[PDB]
Length: 105
Image (cartoon, rainbow, N blue to C red; front, side, top):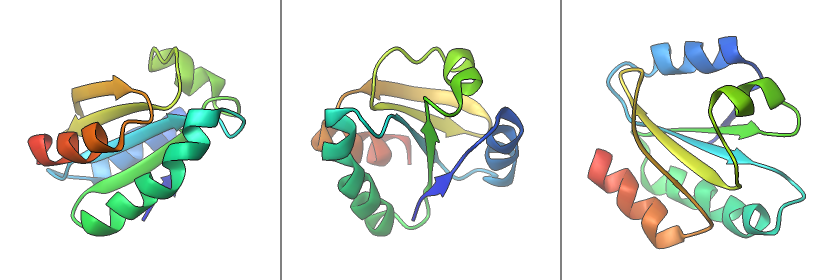
């Protein structure tokens, strides 16, 4: 389903552990309306796409991770393959989320 990532070390470990699998990271804030709107879906997609690793980073708790990641809006989705960022977009756009998961593997 979804793993909460709570430090830069945990982030790097998850990217390393993923091997060749696509990783999708939701940079989110609990208070933010579009994040509330997408949250159950990000979850649903994670069950439809069971070979994809789904991560969440709370930007208010993990401010250093959010800074490093160059986040400026929420939700922001970043996509990784073998440690490399291969896609990114923001907004609670379910169609784009699911399609991007398919485009990147």
